[PDB]
């Protein structure tokens, strides 16, 4: 079995998995909307009661499976629970990261495309008033993606966007086809320091921003001034538990799969804690110091609330690019911003495609080359739905990327700590540990963590599911149809896997 070569490489690949575009865009917007500095109270709590416990569990489950030659959840769930229904539930740990990959690699390609256009100067140059600067960049994005100009839900990506997507798939494959240590691990040791340098440069340059409308200090101010009155709102605590769960990449199968290349008695307690910490530091220190302070510096604290409500995507793809076109050397600044987002995405997508690759290798005995190429083929092909059908992306992101992962997070806990056995699970986590998990976490993992996840799941199911089902366009059924088909196909592959095993 492939293994991580060095402890540092393992930590950087895992941190690389967790650190993504959300760290630099989603987290700052969530924090501003949910109590500013006060948001750190439920955020740390969520990290301590949900993020950290579940992450350890996924590492444990992964390492446990890897020791027996299985890196994915259909086989691993079955090892923890010898039941047919365990294998079927395990398909979700293959289906979730596959579906997310189908839209994520494409979004990732946008950052590469924007980076290139900025570098060579193929970007708008306004002209005054805020909308006069924002609008040319809104149009730039819309022409790139091919946002529908009619009533048809049809996207028409530019030729540039399509080719960059091809290049982005190629880069992912280039890394993945080299394997865990010589591919994913090797790239982690380059990308994570590169990521750190890019962010630190941006933080310094953003902190120097001074405009007639404000400063970066005003931005840091608006973001970090506590509003403890928002702590009464349960939706702020839901937002925190959700933000932590998504930022750490829990429930995607990626962590389990990556952990399966950790040797049987190699530490996961300290390595896991360190990886999660890297993600948090990148999130609150770097992510919180770039996008929002930059936006508030240029548009003024008066528009801070409006900026936050316009969302993470507009901030990262419209607002910030517009600001850069109005700042000195902003052209090279825009390149760095999107180069940073690209590496953030790239380190996450290679990790997110590994479960499908590992399944083909482990259960269908494909060579790494064949497993990588076929996985890429399925993802490349399916992505055409995301590129050409308006709102298809959102539909996939809701079922697999939002509802899916929390359901799968809960399923993991129950199978491991309740069905497999809490005592067997606890020993599995702490074995080989450089440090031991605090005894208090035995109760957290068993009662607190699933409770939190159960509550989040129900709240979101009651809140969002009726909306998606009743108020969306008929074309959502196309996306629902396709992704349900994918689940059928993966179930069949799992069916073929157990049949081959019966023969040999
Ligand atoms: C059917 C799934 C695989 C084939 C999908 C069709 C590929 C579409 O290819 C298209 O080529 C055009 C060149 O003019 C580009 O401008 C489009 O953006 C690109 O998507
Ligand atoms: C769901 C898979 C996506 C199908 C790929 C669309 C291929 C459409 O193909 C071409 O599209 C061009 C604009 O896109 C048009 O100029 C052409 O008339 C059309 O033939
Ligand atoms: C972390 C933030 C980056 C992810 C945000 C990408 C999601 C944006 O996807 C959106 O799909 C829409 C469908 O109607 C299009 O109209 C939008 O213009 C397109 O940006
Ligand atoms: O960027 C992801 C991720 C997950 C899977 C893939 Cl294939 C690609 C990227 C992601 C997407 C959506 C929601 C959360 C997360 C996430 N957390 C860590 C890496 N990662
Ligand atoms: Na993250
Ligand atoms: Na990443």
Image (cartoon, helix red, strand yellow):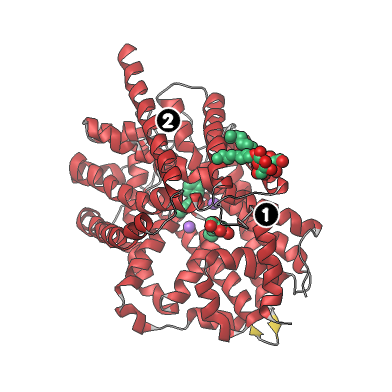
Residue 309 image offset from top left, x and y in percent: 50, 74
Question: Residue at 41% across / 78% down in the picture?
Answer: 35
Packing grade of label 1 (10 A; few <14, some 14-19, many >=20) is many
Picture layout, residue 445 above or below residue 290 = above
Residue placed most toward the observer, 270 or 363: 363
Where is residue 82 drawn, in percent x and y? 21, 30
Instruction: Give coordinates of residue 19: x percent, y percent.
Output: 52, 55
Quadrant where the N terminus is found in the figure: top left
Give the camera-side residue of 313 and 239. Answer: 313
The residue shown at (71%, 56%) is 115
Horizontal side of 396 relative to 73 (left or right) equals right
Q: Are marks 1 and 2 in contact (CB under 8 Å)?
A: no
Q: Give the crowd class for mark 2: few <14, some 14-19, many >=20 residues within 10 Å.
A: many
Name, please, the residue furthest toward the front. 151
Which residue does the numbered mark 2 point to in the structure image? 359
Q: Quadrant of residue 415?
A: top left
Residue 440 located left or right of residue 435: left
- Residue 339, which numbered label? none
Residue 405 picture location, percent across and down: 37, 50
Image quarter hosting the C terminus: top left
Residue 228 in view of the camera: yes
> Residue at (72%, 60%) from the top-left corner?
335
Query: What residue would you read off at disc 1?
Result: 144
Taking the spot 67% from the left edge, 51% from the top edge, the residue there is 112
Q: Find numbered disc 2 in the image and state the secondary structure of the residue it sits on.
A: helix
Q: Secondary structure at mark 1?
A: helix
- Disc 1 versus disc 2: nearer the observer: 1
- Alpha carbon separation for disc pair 1 and 2: 35 Å
Farthest residue to the top: give it.
503
Above or below, 147 relative to 322: above
Query: Is any atom of residue 163 visible in this view?
Result: no
Relative to the observer, which residue lies in front, 406 or 200? 406
């Amino acid at each position: 079995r492939e293994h991580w070569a060095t402890r540092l490489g393992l930590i950087l690949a895992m941190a690389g998995y967790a650190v993504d575009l959300g760290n630099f865009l989603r987290f700052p917007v969530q924090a501003a909307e949910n109590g500013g500095g006060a948001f750190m109270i439920p955020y740390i709590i969520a990290f301590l009661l949900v993020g950290i416990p579940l992450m350890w569990i996924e590492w444990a489950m992964g390492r446990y499976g890897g020791a027996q030659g299985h890196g994915t959840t259909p086989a691993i769930f079955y090892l923890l629970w010898r039941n047919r229904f365990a294998k079927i539930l395990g398909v979700f740990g293959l289906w979730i990261p596959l579906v997310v990959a189908i839209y994520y690699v494409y979004i990732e390609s946008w950052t590469l495309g924007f980076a290139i256009k900025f570098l060579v100067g193929l970007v708008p140059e306004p002209p005054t008033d805020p909308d006069s600067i924002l609008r040319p960049f809104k149009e730039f994005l819309y022409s790139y993606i091919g946002v529908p100009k009619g009533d048809e839900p049809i996207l028409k990506p530019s030729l540039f966007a399509y080719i960059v997507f091809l290049i982005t798939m190629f880069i992912n494959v280039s890394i993945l086809i080299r394997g865990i240590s010589k591919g994913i691990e090797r790239f982690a040791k380059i990308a994570m320091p590169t990521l750190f340098i890019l962010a630190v440069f941006l933080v310094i340059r953003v902190f120097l921003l001074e405009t007639p409308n404000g400063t970066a200090a005003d931005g840091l101010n608006f973001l970090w001034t506590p509003d403890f009155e928002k702590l009464k709102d349960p939706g702020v605590w839901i937002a925190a538990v959700g933000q932590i769960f998504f930022s750490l990449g829990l429930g995607f199968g990626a962590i389990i799969t990556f952990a399966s290349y950790v040797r049987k008695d190699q530490d996961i307690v300290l390595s896991g804690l360190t990886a999660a910490t890297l993600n948090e530091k990148a999130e609150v220190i770097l992510g919180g110091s770039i996008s929002i302070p930059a936006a508030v510096a240029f548009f003024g604290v008066a528009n801070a609330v409006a900026i936050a409500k316009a969302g993470a995507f507009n901030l990262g793809f419209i607002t910030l690019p517009a600001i850069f076109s109005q700042t000195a050397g902003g052209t090279f600044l825009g390149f760095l911003w999107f180069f940073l987002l690209f590496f953030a995405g790239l380190t996450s997508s290679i990790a997110g495609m590994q479960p499908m690759i590992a399944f083909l290798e482990d259960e269908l005995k494909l060579s790494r080359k064949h497993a990588v190429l076929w996985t890429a083929a399925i993802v490349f092909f399916s992505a055409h739905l995301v590129m050409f059908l308006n709102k298809s992306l959102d539909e996939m992101d809701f079922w697999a990327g939002t509802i899916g992962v929390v359901f799968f997070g809960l399923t993991e806990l129950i199978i491991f700590f309740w069905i497999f056995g809490a005592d067997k699970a606890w020993e599995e986590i702490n074995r080989g540990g450089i440090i031991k998990v605090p005894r208090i976490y035995y109760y957290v993992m068993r009662y607190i963590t699933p409770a939190f996840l159960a509550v989040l799941l129900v709240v979101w199911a009651r809140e969002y599911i009726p909306k998606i089902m009743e108020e969306t366009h008929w074309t959502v059924w196309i996306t629902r149809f396709y992704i349900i088909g994918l689940f059928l196909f993966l179930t069949f592959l799992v069916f073929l896997a157990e049949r081959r095993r019966n023969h040999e």
